[PDB]
Length: 6
Length: 164
Image (cartoon, rainbow over all chains, first blue to last red; front, side):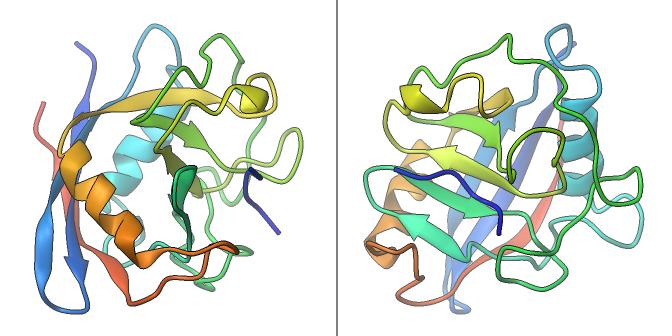
């Protein structure tokens, strides 16, 4: 799973 | 000159507006080209029709996966993935266009548009662009996000292309 986190 | 592309956003049919971006040339000659050729839809695939599956208010709007529409698909113009170009540019503030990934050397087609300063992302994510205008359309796609990133409606890239 791809994606930046807060 | 540095390319300029755009997206024509929609919100479940009902068009929203346009967001254009200034890809970077001298900074990212291989990463910007990727996003360019995709913004266009230059090979039978690209962002045309794809959506923003993960939108987090105050942080970012994420999209790019035209394949599985979730956060697993997508793919660069070199098959599927490509190395971390460089980390010369940093997540300085809203509008910053940056590559979404899954750690180092995992750049597909996925990206996110920051809606605040996301400094912790520097070094971890390749910055390769910035919203030129339509940062108002972007701030309007937020009223449809959430805590986990789930789209409260259906934000679509009704169109996209290169103007310069």
